[PDB]
Image (cartoon, rainbow, N blue to C red; front, side):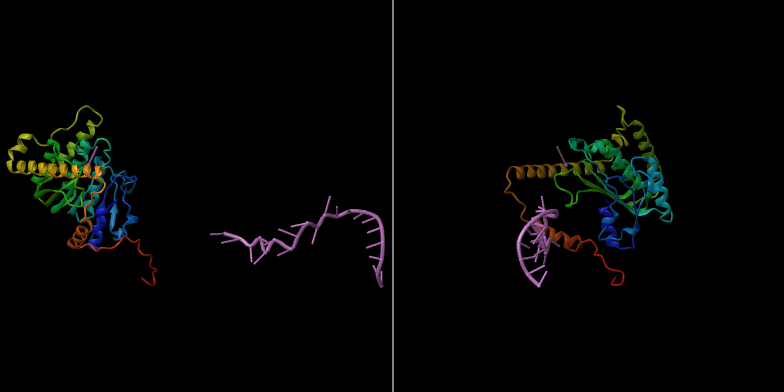
Amino acid sequence: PGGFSEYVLWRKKWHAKGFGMTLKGPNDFKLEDFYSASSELFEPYYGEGGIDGDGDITRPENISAFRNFVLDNTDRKGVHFLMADGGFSVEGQENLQEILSKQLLLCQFLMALSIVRTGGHFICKTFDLFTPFSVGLVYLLYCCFERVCLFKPITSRPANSERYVVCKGLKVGIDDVRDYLFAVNIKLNQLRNTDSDVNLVVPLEVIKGDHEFTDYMIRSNESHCSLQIKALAKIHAFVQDTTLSEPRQAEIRKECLRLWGIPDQARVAPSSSDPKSK
RNA sequence: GGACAUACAUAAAGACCAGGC
């Protein structure tokens, strides 16, 4: 429901304009619930048919209609940055979350190359990144941007595979990689419910030929696994012994809010002012 | 991965009988 958007709109007030696309349903944009931000500065668009579309990011037509709409609403330049927080329930298949979400990862990366301006930025949620498919998608972003990193914020839960790819400075000439990833998404859609799938988007010999990329990718995965293993074992110990507690949670909270410049206040429904007093 | 039924209301009706001015 656009929690990420609320912070950006609240931080920049009206000096910002947001464009949204998400699946219609229980997890649609709750623009009414933006208590800290002016929801009028945001515009949801659900692909083909605009407001009446389904918002399927994996579907190409939703991407295309949104793509034309976003470029038009940005003087044909695109957005300064894209945020992407895609995920769905994998209840009882948590170990397969990467493989199950692979097309959603691709479509969010394709969306970055479709609507981010030159010199613009991208941030996308991902999970595990073990498969050559997911690593080849990160390699294409590393080619297309001045700088890329894999980052797990402390606001992500330590025991889950959730991390963010963060890309800074979209290069010129990314059109071929965009149109390639658009063709790969069409191929994934054709292979839905078949015994075949797209297993590579960059050859393993190309990825492993960049030793500097490969040495970062391995080290990022193994460091994340090591921290996730400790955090999973910690949760298991805190199930077995219910007297265990983190004593510093209230201290760490106060310091994080101070550091990030976030006021320590409760969520209050605006207040209803009358138009004369306001 | 909350109420004073402040509903004063039991008044059968109907009948005959007795008395009052």
